[PDB]
Length: 124
Image 1 (spheres, rainbow, N blue to C red):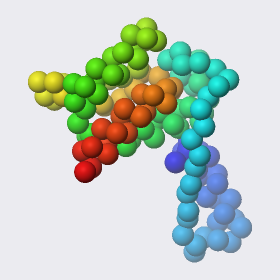
Image 2 (image 1 turned 135 degrees about the vertical axis):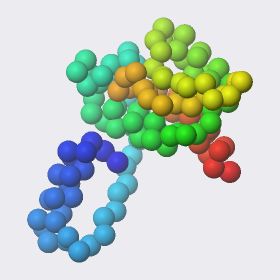
Image 3 (image 1 turned 60 degrees about the vertical axis):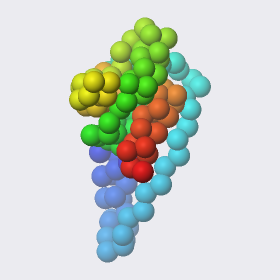
């Protein structure tokens, strides 16, 4: 996905082009941000729209996904390493949590890896 407004713009554009009866196809490419660093920014404070889409996309994929204490631990290191808490975790188990929301519109690729793997774990 992408931002609601751009998604609607891309879709309206295709409909205007007379492909309304056609089914939509969506594919995107993850890119690493080598321009700016992770600083817990929001759109209002400098986060790129694509950064917010990335972060929110990962967030969506881990909705209700159980995070073990090992997962939580890894995120915690990043939190320490960046001296900033980017997650709203809800205690659901002695050592398990659930991510309910983010604290910024940025997410490091390393953190996304941990989270997406928890999602795949629960899946399998």
